[PDB]
Image (cartoon, rainbow over all chains, first blue to last red):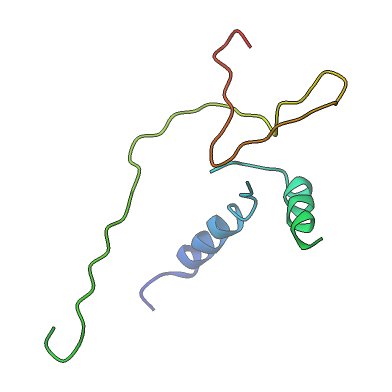
Length: 41
Length: 48
C-alpha cells in the first residue's frame, strides 16, 4: 500500500484527537460528552 | 466537461493563527443571568 501502517495509524490518531470540538476549541472529553448530551433533550 | 461535470468550489482556508484562551460563558456574580457566544468567542484583553 501507498502509506505505511504507522502513517495510517498516525492519521487515525490525529482524527481521534479532534473529536472534542463543540460550540477550533480544545475541550475535555467529559465536557464534550455533556455538551453532546444536552442537544438530544 | 468532457463526459461529465467540472466542479469548482471556493473555500476559506485560514492561514495564520494565534494562541488565545476563552471561557464557557460570562455570567452574573450570584449566577443570576449568564450569556454565551453566538458564532464567536469571548477573549479577555488582559485587564479583565
